Structure formats: C-alpha cells, structure tokens
Image (cartoon, rainbow, N blue to C red; front, top):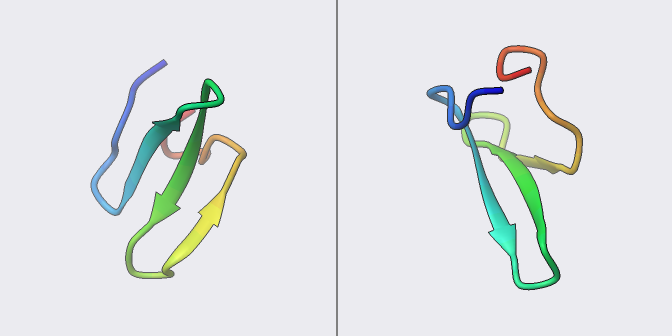
Length: 37
C-alpha cells in the first residue's frame, strides 16, 4: 500500500483518517485511488 502518487496525495486528519486529494481534478475523496491502491 503506497502513498502519494503524483497528482494524488493523502493527508491524515486529527480524527485519525486520510483524505485523498487529486490536484488537477481538485477533488477530495476518502476512498483510496486505484492508481494508489
């Protein structure tokens, strides 16, 4: 299970979970990208 593939990067929030942010979509999803899964 890798982390941060280019355009996709995830940060863990204080509540203890990562949100996956795609930069050139500008989208934020709580599901692991299939390029990063």
